[PDB]
Length: 155
Image 1 (cartoon, helix red, strand yellow):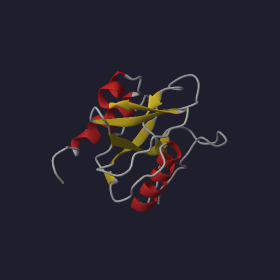
Image 2 (image 1 turned 135 degrees about the vertical axis):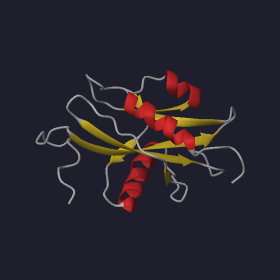
Image 3 (image 1 turned 90 degrees about the vertical axis):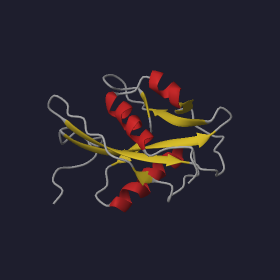
Image 4 (image 1 turned 90 degrees about the horizontal axis):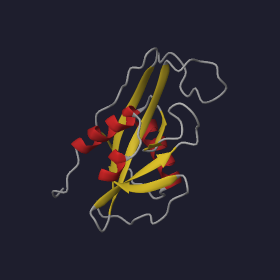
């Protein structure tokens, strides 16, 4: 009985109070070692026009979420795996009179083919580059979480 509506983007009807989204972290091997991807929103104003990992609307089904979750990612990079995707914890930030629910997702290319492609709305930075990057707390929290289950060690 999921009450409330998801995706206040459309015609302003429901309050932001109920806002859920599923963000994922895309990483790929490089000369240095491994760099992640960071996209910026066209929005302008408060918490608008900032850099942060790509995300998609919230899905009730553990499958629908991952499915669409990738769709977006592809829009930026392109070829995105499926099995490599795995949910790693979550990030829920409580605002003054609002409640946001971000789903932390990790996705890295063990040894698959690179993307060597990206639109003018997405930039490929490193792990140390992201931090210094202007990112909203919410997002900054998703990273530390994604780092958890992630290591170079064999697999």
